[PDB]
């Protein structure tokens, strides 16, 4: 059997690059007798206990397959083999070109007595000289460890060592070394000792690990990593995009680095007035944009990813879309039904919980802070429409808190010590008999000037519809949104999804071979996570980044994630566990998902549960194809090393916590897997894709509070009485930070046209050999089609008002699919923004 037809498909560097090529470039084109060489490794025949490798073969072709793909080149080789080489199930490759190419696949056809073999690569191959060992790629055969080809056990073992790479050295672009390190690269201690931030990782501050980058330490701090112009992530975790509009992390680097300078100059040099006057000025943002004169612009130029990214037509511009929560009822945002609806069906839809006892305690110590008990008590909780006692309403599963109190208090002196004036809130909600919630009171806690020990200085507030007191209710509500928007951005979003998924991406690539059942299960749920977190570490959660300067906890934000993380339990992220812990549901096996929801028209948890079991059934089906027993899941060395390093290093600051699955069990594997995918896919989508639709109007979702509350016939109070729009505007997020906020969260809410949503979407039809899982993944994808149909139904039911509101905004967030753009819908597989 003479020649086996290999035919390789690839994408060139200039095609997945934001700048490279013209027309005629860095298009790298005429390939022949060396440019690329391939050796075939044997699955069947050995030399020792290692498959035969067979003769460097040049890529003697270059034309059409003819359905190759958009901007994909395909090569061809005729490999001279026989039979005593055996069947190939792996290959080594060498790039002799200057440029790297994106290798997609290699199909091995016309192999005698055997079928056409598939290699799914989706990896870049840089020049041969960058590598000690040449690139190895296995065929699409899923193999548990004690299921490897005996010529291939040593290449599989060898390949996982090279991805692991020792814990030394400064990492390069072309590398694929997954290793961990603490968050010690957020500060810039050398260019001022005020930009120095603490390490998030270890004894003192618990946190997950980030990808190791190995740059040099700082001059002033030997235990903190210097900044870099390039932040490293394992090469294949940074995805290119065939289209320029889809480099959204690049458009967010370019906000932080490029747009922000211009704004800083325009405000400073007064090309722009520093603060908004009416609420009609704020709405014009979305009606005509941020304008600036020709001469200023033609000098401070260009930043072209803010292209038809913001579609800034002509000139004298920057441009925002009208947010959905303002598209149809412009003032819907003021209404207490929209204020409370958004707790259940908004931007940050999972903080709220049941009230178990009353008064309402403080879980912080009295010798150091005091009596931080809630002063929302009994009197003001019995209103217009509220026949029950507080004691009947908790009895009846009708009274709810939004506690933004105790995590805030130790950090509040510190938060308020400069340009930001704020409270540590608490907010009681009543589930009205109509299925909707409403606010019954807000205690605003202020620090207390005679020390932390005689604090707080609390003030309760209740609904109002009269004169000036209307606006005091509004400002009381904004001091709660302010508290929540930064609990969102940081905890519900950065820590709970982005930050805690990183150790999973790293632990899977280091201990679970690219050929493993479970590597391939998890794998599509990691798409661009390491890339958006490396740019978040460089341009968003850094000393003076967009998150500190735009959101309330400021310089203390990420230090606060570490302490809130002291309480992060992985088990409770699973959506049943979550609901059951907050008390907005109970385990009722008679009920549809095995849980009865106490707030029954809670749109996030209602659609959520539908998507949770859709994920959990598939990973259970999948896992069953590969483990017929708990005792053979235990018998897997890679999997047990995956979970061992994950819980011990990855999230090692909680490594001795009692809730960690110990992976002795197939159901332990199934919930561990499903929780992860939930976090990566649906949770993240729930808390992220509704950021510009809801918080794209600072009125509706204010990020910073600059003044405190007007008291009683105060000059502040009479100024608010005179014109209340302006004093409100003076309390919340002022213009400059409104603009940087808005530009980030708009990009952050966009779906790239090349996005991979849950279902149907992985990389290739032949990502595995196994026919069972392939068809079990089309059924899971059909299942989501069906579930979307049930969700589309609940948004035509005009009975469920919580999924519409004063805002008239059908809660489209957990709809598993979507078109590109800034839809209020779609569930990607992963944290891709
Ligand atoms: Fe995100």
Image (cartoon, rainbow, N blue to C red):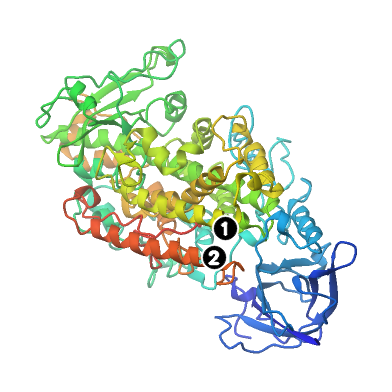
Q: Is ligand 1 closer than 8 angstroms to the Cβ of mark 2? A: no
Q: Secondary structure at mark 1?
A: helix
Query: Is the residue 383 above or below the residue 189 in the image?
Result: above
Which residue corresponds to mark 2? 772
Instruction: Give neighbour class at mark 1: few <14, some 14-19, many 20+ (Cα, 10 Å).
Output: few
Quarter of the picture containing the N terminus is: bottom right
* Quarter-of-image position of residue 412: top left
* CB atoms of marks 2 and 1 within 8 Å: yes
- Residue 704: x and y in percent read 38, 39
Q: Is residue 758 above or below residue 207?
A: below
Please state if 823 lies on the left or on the right of 728 as rendered.
right
Does residue 3 appear in the picture of this structure?
Answer: yes
Placement of 750 over or under 423, stated as above or below: below
Dot 2 crowding, Cα within 10 Å, few <14, some 14–19, many 20+ = few
Q: Is residue 371 left or right of residue 152?
A: left
**Residue with the mark numbered 1:** 625
The residue sitting at 71% across, 72% down in the picture is 100
Q: CA distance from mark 2 to mark 1?
A: 7 Å
Q: Nearer the viewer, residue 170 or 135?
A: 135
Residue 718 placed where, x, y %?
A: 18, 31
Apparent side of residue 265 relative to residue 434 in the rendered image (left or right): right
687 vs 68, nearest the viewer: 68
Residue at 62 percent across and 38 percent down: it is 647
Find residue 146 and report its image quarter: bottom right
Residue at image location 52% in from the left, 45% down from the top: 545
């Amino acid at each position: 059997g003479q020649k086996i037809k290999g035919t390789m498909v690839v994408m060139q560097k200039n095609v997945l690059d934001i700048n490279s090529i013209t027309s005629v470039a860095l298009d790298t084109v005429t390939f022949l007798a060396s440019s690329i060489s391939i050796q075939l490794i044997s699955a069947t025949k050995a030399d020792g206990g290692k498959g035969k490798v067979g003769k460097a073969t040049n890529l003697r072709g270059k034309i059409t397959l003819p359905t190759i793909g958009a901007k994909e080149e395909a090569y061809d080789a005729q490999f001279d083999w026989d039979s005593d080489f055996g069947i190939p199930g792996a290959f080594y490759i060498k790039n002799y070109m200057q440029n790297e190419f994106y290798l997609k696949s290699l199909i091995l056809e016309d192999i005698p007595n055997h079928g056409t073999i598939h290699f799914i690569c989706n990896s870049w191959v840089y020049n041969s000289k960058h590598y000690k060992t040449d690139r190895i790629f296995f065929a699409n055969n899923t193999y548990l460890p004690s299921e490897t080809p005996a010529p291939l056990v040593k290449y599989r073992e060898e390949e996982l060592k090279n991805v692991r790479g020792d814990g030394t050295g400064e990492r390069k672009e072309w590398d694929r070394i997954y290793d961990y390190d603490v968050y010690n690269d957020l500060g810039d201690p050398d260019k001022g000792e005020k930009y120095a931030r603490p390490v998030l990782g270890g004894s003192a501050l618990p946190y997950p690990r980030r990808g190791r980058t190995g740059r040099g330490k700082t001059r002033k701090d030997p235990n903190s990593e210097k900044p870099g112009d390039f932040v490293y992530l394992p090469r294949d975790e940074a995805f290119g995009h065939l289209k320029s509009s889809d480099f959204l992390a690049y458009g967010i680097k370019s906000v932080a680095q490029d747009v922000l300078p211009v704004l800083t100059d325009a405000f400073d040099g007064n090309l722009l007035s520093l603060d908004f006057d009416n609420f009609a000025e704020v709405r014009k943002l979305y009606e005509g944009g941020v304008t600036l004169p020709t001469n200023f612009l033609s000098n401070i130029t260009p930043i072209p990813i803010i292209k038809e990214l913001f579609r800034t037509d002509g000139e004298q511009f920057l441009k925002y879309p009208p947010p959905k929560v303002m598209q149809v009822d412009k003032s819907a945002w003021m209404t207490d039904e929209e204020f409370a609806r958004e707790t259940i069906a908004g931007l940050n839809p999972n903080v709220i919980k049941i009230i178990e006892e009353f008064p309402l305690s403080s879980k912080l110590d009295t010798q150091a802070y005091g009596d931080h008990t809630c002063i929302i008590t009994k009197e003001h909780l019995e209103p217009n429409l509220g026949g029950l006692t507080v004691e009947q309403a908790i009895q009846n599963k009708k009274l709810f808190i939004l506690d933004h109190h105790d995590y805030l208090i130790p950090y509040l002196r510190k938060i308020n010590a400069n340009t930001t004036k704020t409270y540590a809130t608490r907010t009681i909600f009543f589930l009205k008999n109509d299925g909707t919630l409403t606010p019954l009171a807000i205690e605003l806690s202020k620090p207390h000037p005679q020390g932390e020990e005689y604090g707080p200085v609390s003030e309760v507030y209740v609904p109002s519809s009269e004169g000036v007191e209307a606006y005091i209710w509004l400002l009381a509500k904004a001091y709660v949104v302010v508290n929540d928007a930064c609990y969102h951005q940081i905890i519900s979003h950065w820590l709970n999804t982005h930050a805690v998924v990183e150790p999973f991406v790293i632990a899977t690539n280091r201990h679970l071979s690219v050929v493993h059942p479970i590597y391939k299960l998890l794998f599509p749920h990691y798409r661009d996570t390491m890339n958006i977190n490396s740019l978040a570490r460089k341009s968003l959660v850094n000393a003076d980044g967009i998150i500190e300067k735009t959101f309330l906890w400021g310089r203390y934000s990420l230090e606060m994630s570490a302490v809130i993380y002291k309480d992060w339990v992985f088990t409770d992220q699973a959506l049943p566990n979550d609901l059951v812990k907050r008390g907005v549901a109970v385990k009722d096996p008679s009920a549809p998902h095995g849980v009865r929801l106490l707030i029954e028209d809670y749109p996030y948890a209602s659609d959520g549960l539908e998507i949770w079991d859709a994920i959990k059934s598939w990973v259970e089906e999948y896992v069953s194809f590969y483990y017929k027993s708990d005792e053979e899941l235990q018998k897997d060395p890679e999997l047990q090393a995956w979970w061992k390093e994950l819980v011990e290093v990855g999230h090692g600051d909680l490594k001795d916590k009692p809730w960690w699955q110990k992976m002795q069990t197939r159901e332990e594997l199934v919930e561990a897997s499903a929780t992860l995918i939930w976090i990566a896919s649906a949770l993240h989508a729930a808390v992220n894709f509704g950021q510009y639709p809801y918080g794209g109007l600072i009125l509706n979702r204010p990020t910073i509070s600059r003044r405190f509350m007007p008291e009683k016939g105060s000059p502040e109070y009479d100024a608010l009485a005179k014109n209340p729009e302006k004093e409100f505007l003076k309390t919340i997020t002022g213009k400059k930070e409104t603009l940087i906020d808005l530009t980030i969260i708009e990009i952050l809410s966009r779906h790239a046209s090349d996005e991979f949503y849950l279902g149907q979407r992985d990389g290739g039809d032949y990502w595995t050999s196994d026919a069972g899982p392939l068809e079990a993944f089309k059924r899971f994808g059909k299942n989501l089609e069906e579930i979307e149909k049930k969700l589309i139904e609940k948004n035509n039911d005009e009975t469920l008002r919580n999924r519409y509101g004063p805002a008239k905004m059908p809660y489209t967030l957990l709809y598993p699919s979507s078109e590109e753009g800034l839809t209020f819908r779609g569930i990607p597989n992963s944290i891709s923004i």
